[PDB]
Image (cartoon, rainbow, N blue to C red):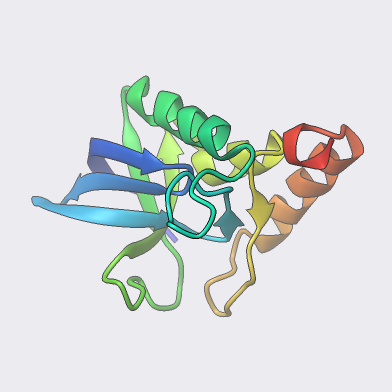
Length: 135
């Protein structure tokens, strides 16, 4: 894998951000993580939804460099969203969310699962510490 630069356009919610990537706007879905929802007519705002959303948002808005990392499998989903690991000044947003109890490790689809173990380790630590979703 390798990182490529992108520019923030808009944070959307906890696990979706809009970036400029190679000259075009693109919506990116964060690989391997599930955050509580802020929209979606179903329940609308699930618990910790607004918190994960503000966390993702502050982390990418305060960054001086954003990088995207595609995994080895498909790089877009059926909704045309890019599927990637997002880095803010060198720190993976996907792991930070999980480390803080603000996301769970998603259902995993090989071969898009390179950072699966790292993330499950951060999730177990957040569980032990009983943070946010785990309290």
